[PDB]
Image: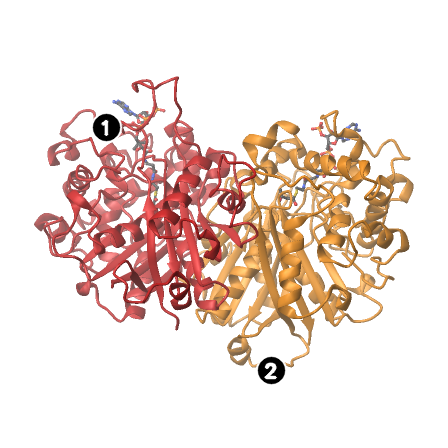
Chain colours: A red, B orange
Amino acid sequence: ASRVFIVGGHITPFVGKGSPLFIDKKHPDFGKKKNMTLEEILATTVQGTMEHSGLSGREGIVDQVVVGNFLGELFSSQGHLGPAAIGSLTYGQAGSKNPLMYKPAMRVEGAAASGGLAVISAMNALKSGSADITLAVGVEVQTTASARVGGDYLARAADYQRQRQLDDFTFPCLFAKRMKYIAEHNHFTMEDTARVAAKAYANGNKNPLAHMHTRKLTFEQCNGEDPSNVKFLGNETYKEYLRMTDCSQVSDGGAGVVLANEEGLRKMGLSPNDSRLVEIKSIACAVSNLYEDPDDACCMFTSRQAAQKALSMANIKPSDLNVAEVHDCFTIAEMLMYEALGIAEYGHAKDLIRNGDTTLEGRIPVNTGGGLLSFGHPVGATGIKQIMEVYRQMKGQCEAYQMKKIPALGATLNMGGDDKTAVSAVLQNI
Amino acid sequence: ASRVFIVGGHITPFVGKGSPLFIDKKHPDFGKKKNMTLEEILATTVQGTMEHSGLSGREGIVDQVVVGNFLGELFSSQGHLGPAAIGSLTYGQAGSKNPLMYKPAMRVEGAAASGGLAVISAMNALKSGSADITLAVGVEVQTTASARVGGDYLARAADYQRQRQLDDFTFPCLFAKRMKYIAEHNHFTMEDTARVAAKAYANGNKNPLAHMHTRKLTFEQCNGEDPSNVKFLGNETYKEYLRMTDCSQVSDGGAGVVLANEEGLRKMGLSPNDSRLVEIKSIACAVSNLYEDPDDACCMFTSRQAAQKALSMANIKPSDLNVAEVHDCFTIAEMLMYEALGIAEYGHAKDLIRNGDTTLEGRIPVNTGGGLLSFGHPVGATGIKQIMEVYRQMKGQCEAYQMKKIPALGATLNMGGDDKTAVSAVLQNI
Ligand SMILES: CC(=O)CC(=O)SCCNC(=O)CCNC(=O)[C@H](O)C(C)(C)COP(=O)(O)OP(=O)(O)OC[C@H]1O[C@@H](n2cnc3c(N)ncnc32)[C@H](O)[C@@H]1OP(=O)(O)O
Ligand SMILES: CC(=O)CC(=O)SCCNC(=O)CCNC(=O)[C@H](O)C(C)(C)COP(=O)(O)OP(=O)(O)OC[C@H]1O[C@@H](n2cnc3c(N)ncnc32)[C@H](O)[C@@H]1OP(=O)(O)O
């Protein structure tokens, strides 16, 4: 087994409605300057990743590139992101010399798990001998359509034939449906989900890259007492179980990471104990059946399978973790992710949230920079953002949201669709 | 280096307008039954692949699944094909036991090179120790939109912002644009491309899986002598250089392959010298810049890079090949692929086609079952179909289009976009 190391990476600001970085009718530059395109975000991500990893001027030592992206063919009319990434180093300098020419590249997809699947592909390439240094980048632009057209696009992650009819906001409806069953079993409550949102927004207020950085929300606002916090679904069966503040943001952004094996480190002139490295101890993927849903909506079975495989392969227990990043696409999902990861037992996520165990001051901080709720959710980027967030904490780089006790062990859990794809990784600080 | 073996596979009939298998006004079942959906095609492909590979009843020994698909999100409103593949063994049998539950799965994409990229991802998993048996499947449904809407969807493979404006049929226009430069340099002629189509259709007439199986074309109906073979492009600059018979078909279908390492063969009860096997000696991927095109339209630089890497890794020369499958998305591309692969020198593909060298009776038969022109082109399936076509000839399984001499060595060359992604493999018979 060849060891795999994160050498460095980059996360863009995540932007959309409500960010002062987003150009809309309220913005000074409206009509004069535009928001970044998918191509521009990909170029900023690739370049920033190479720069932060020490590869500027020697990008030719990267052996291959993997791009995670979910819906570029719909939001930007652009597939084939492999060769877009090959062109990203020199984007806008037509005819410049391009050290990535002719290298392997491809795009991987598994809905919001696309970024995590990109890291898996990159790692297989490292362990198979076909690469010693790999670039994995995840990007998404979703702000180019209305929220309602965007909802139909996102519904590509569901069993579209079977489930699109639930609601124009198909995904929010699928999680409202879970939350209804959850509330009926008293597994946890809408108050508890309001506590998740309060935590996410307080964390994002410490994070200048966060979509909702400037938005301050109290527990009371998240719990439905602000009348701007609407129960917005059309489906009358499920609409009482999802507020706006329960939902991840519609964001644009990118995240990238450079991965290396022991031979890659040697080429870069680095030792395996270099203080800039994090080891990926394990990574695992589990996928369930798109066409059939388990009866027990209180459990994310697929996410749990992936987390168990990863922790087992790394030979650690959930109680060994010092930090985690989980797929909080709704407040509802974070709670379930506590239990999928195993930092709470089944029915005890509510204990963790009521006691502050996952806050920055808690014994197991989760989603320290705002998660999908506040940091934002450019779908393809998210799995790589999670990895880089853990890396940033382990390297002391998080500024106002830096954990005081540098974490030795971390985990990520990245989910696609209604718990149909899951990717989980265990990271160990060097 | 772990060796990789093709254990078996399956190709569906490829269907669309002009096939008696396509349900349209001419078909007995018109109005009563519908053409297969993407889900149904994926289920038929996964089940057929398992069946032909000897895995029926033991599908649990498959460690992972990779799906090639380009445009399901547009043509079928469905992404996230990983969990669709997990549900494909038991499709339509709700509640049945599913030995693939929780295995890794993902979708990979690189336009028409998606099927080839799927094979590469599967092979990296086999060589990395995370898998011993893998399933790679490629599927596409494009008959759900008109050929013109479909053209806009296919333009996702181009630099959409830069190139969509050429023509509604963006890809046919990019290849017409090549052909104009090609014709001006006398590199080869429209007569030569007509000879490619005559070959493809005669091959497809021997192949019951072919989209154009029942369509017989004389050379005169390929060479523009028949005015009903229309020059259909809107762009006046390029419209003279492309006839309908020059174009790959808009098809629906699937192809699958089971791949194994030495450990996988052991699990299956097979020896590495078993007569059902074909070794994949090498596979390689090269990707160029989406945003910039080379000046020399007479050369497919990216395709040539991938073929050279694969031949070199296998330690063979082009003159050692007994059979090949190349990416004939237009008659124009087949000609250029002869020279990318190296079975002709630059400017000499025309010699091969004028002398019959790539016919079934020739010294190096290419696209023996009709290629993308007659077999058809469900884009995600194509890379895997190519592999399976070489396999089928090596195993004597091609019936009316079986070669005169069993091939010992074969190659494939699969391309995405306008020579932006290329995947090439070398196969050796056992
Ligand atoms: C599935 C996995 O794998 C895990 C995942 O990743 S799932 C992916 C999760 N992501 C998503 O689904 C995106 C979720 N988030 C969202 O869609 C948005 O954040 C929202 C939650 C939709 C945000 O809303 P917004 O940005 O303010 O946009 P907006 O245009 O106002 O849309 C809200 C809708 O609610 C209603 N609404 C909003 N404000 C309202 C008010 N004050 N009064 C009444 N109704 C209101 C409206 O009907 C509106 O749509 P219409 O104008 O078409 O009616
Ligand atoms: C992107 C990647 O990476 C993938 C690749 O490998 S590259 C992409 C390769 N694939 C393609 O580009 C698809 C190419 N093929 C096609 O679009 C179609 O097969 C084809 C247009 C060549 C033939 O299509 P068809 O469906 O048999 O005929 P039909 O669909 O009835 O009409 C096709 C068009 O031909 C023309 N046509 C047909 N009959 C005609 C007639 N009697 N008179 C004039 N024009 C006629 C029309 O222009 C028609 O389109 P519109 O009606 O929209 O104007």
Considering depth in this image, is A329 or A301 the residue closer to the camera? A329
Label 1 secondary element:
loop
Q: Position of residue A23 (x, y in %)?
A: 34, 24
**Chain identifier of the residue bearing label 1 in the image:** A
Q: Is residue B222 left or right of residue B208?
A: right
The quarter of the image that holds ligand 2 is top right
Please give the residue where the numbered disc 2 appears in the rendered image: B271
Give the quarter of the image for residue A370.
top left
Q: Give the CA separation, mark 1 to mark 2.
A: 64 Å
Please give the residue where the numbered disc 1 appears in the rendered image: A230
Name which residue lies at 33% across and 53% down: A8
Which residue type does callout 2 highlight? Ser
Q: Can residue A5 be seen in this view?
A: yes
Query: Measured along the vertical axis of the image, is residue B312 above or below residue A397?
Result: below
Q: Position of residue A39 (x, y in %)?
A: 46, 36
Q: Is residue B95 visible?
A: no
Query: Measured along the vertical axis of the image, is residue B158 above or below residue A31?
Result: below
Name which residue lies at 56% across and 46% down: B70
Q: In this view, does B319 lie to the left or right of B150?
A: right
- Whether labels 1 and 2 belong to a single chain: the reply is no
